[PDB]
Length: 50
Length: 49
Length: 50
Image 1 (tube, rainbow over the protein chains, first blue to last red):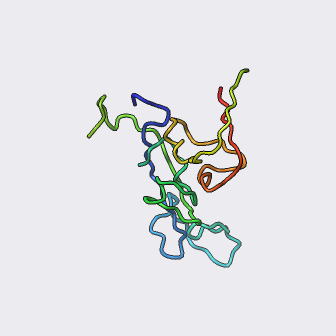
Image 2 (image 1 turned 90 degrees about the vertical axis):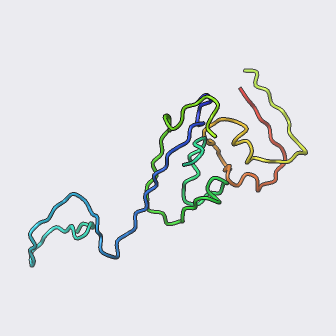
């Protein structure tokens, strides 16, 4: 840092996100909801909303 | 870690000696990049070994 | 207001070395890009500076 403007290095923590096609094993902080069928119900099956 | 003088070497598809022999991103990348300055990494006036 | 324009001709056009001839932070390139700049071949270059 005696010389500056970009002279210091940059820490790079690139994350790679793979689309599912498989068991998920990490999703997010939403917990659960009781299952119900034969009704017009909003979906959050494994991430995609419907 | 990189030199930090340019950070635009970690992106899907450009060429440079920082990221042509070390790291290469594919053209279908679906991730995130985070970068920041490093200050307290080392501290000596003559530089490390 | 008195910016100097200098003519450059008949020399090796190396643009991968101006990265570490100057402590800057990337390019504001319009029309071209610095990654494949050394693969080109054109007439003249002028380096105005102020």
